[PDB]
Image 1: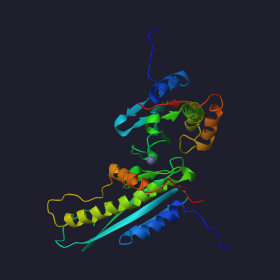
Image 2: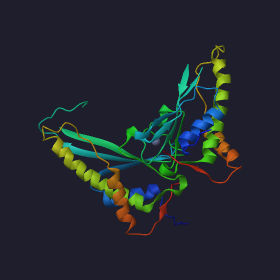
Image 3: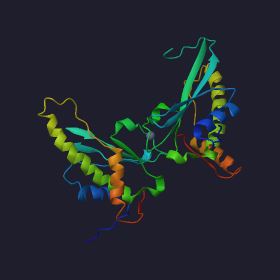
Length: 140
Length: 156
Ligand SMILES: [Zn+2]
């Protein structure tokens, strides 16, 4: 009934993360002091983060995360990218699980990590940016 | 034959560095793989009171300022003094490259001052270099009113 929001990358991610990936312990951390938004994710235990930063104010060590992604401060990011993200993400998680199991039984396996290919991800941004015109989700 | 080329960040920096900061110990590292250009910087000072510092007669302080492609480079912001993003091939507006040069000089001037003060002011706890974005921005603004926008691309 009474549902009305301000459309930020935050709320948008929220919604899209429950409407496309509600099966997972995918969480969100907003470090507003360091203008960053982490997508804490847990697979069942394995935990990695994905980061959104403003290169003009955020401090970051790319290595602590699977991906780092810059947004344009105030403007935020393109919907056609936040989409390509939440989709390519499922790709990486679903593909992540089928290989996470192959780590518990395949004694031939050595280390388990997640694979985020930028190339395939860029392709995802195209895949989605082919349905709607420019839309920009702002940052809080 | 001979060709003529519009400046790129690497050449432009190298050029400006020698032109405006010859008196200082400044180097460049082009990490081609990581799509990154680092400006290395060294201050020296004579140690008299044989003041006891951590880790290590003539002290040396080194630091670095990094240019990176946010779409390409992998970077630990915390390894450098500043971490300046550029726009893939587009590069950076000249005014930014220029504001950088002129602010960097300020930073090293004040740096060398603070260093000498470090070794003689028994009250000084720590010495480092200070990069105030607001002062950087102001430098850029100050140049951006001198001349007309012009971009300086990234090497190929
Ligand atoms: Zn960074």
